[PDB]
Length: 259
Image 1 (cartoon, one colour):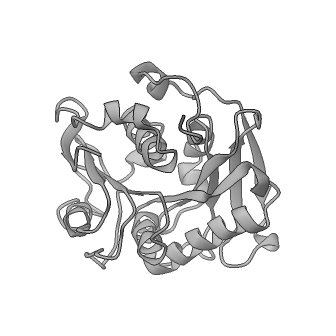
Image 2: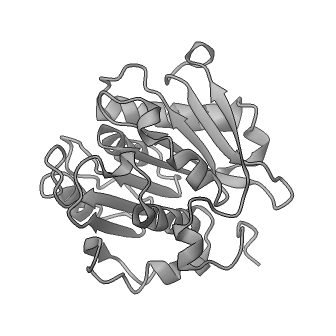
């Protein structure tokens, strides 16, 4: 009935496994071959028999290469998404520049890449770590048609995001000292007055570098948010609404349930 729904009825175990149900193929994008971003790597479900998939562009943070987040490529793609993980023009690009580069990567993916036919160009998303999370907000501010945005430990001197209409899940690290949640993540969250839906997931005792290592709870909520908003997959609302208890590895969760 939902033409964008993919994969089996979900469970906690399906979301916490190292891979989702789709085998993943990969393609490198050379810095020599694109303008507007530094190339990167595309990850996609090998299967085309179940339909096209939505896509997400993901930016690393200041000083970092895509390799700092590479585990996300196969892990997210294996749940039924095309992922373009980017290298930035330089490692020291600021959040606003990272936002423009994420949009350039989505444009390349849908308009020129060798996997464009596998991507539903109407169902796109952005995510990123630290300054790449600040760039995720910048991209959503510029392109209100994006279906999901996931700033991860985001850093941005711009604290307000009234233009953002995209469903936005901010994932903060409670003990982050580089992009403290009290001055970055939480102000950003409170400022998303026009986001169709939003959530704030705070990881208990987590530092700024939590997304550099496979993290099942982070993956569970990122995948659930991507499914619910990129694919309109209401099956994944069971993990988002009612919000999870702030216990164990979650120190805080803020929500706009119902979706």
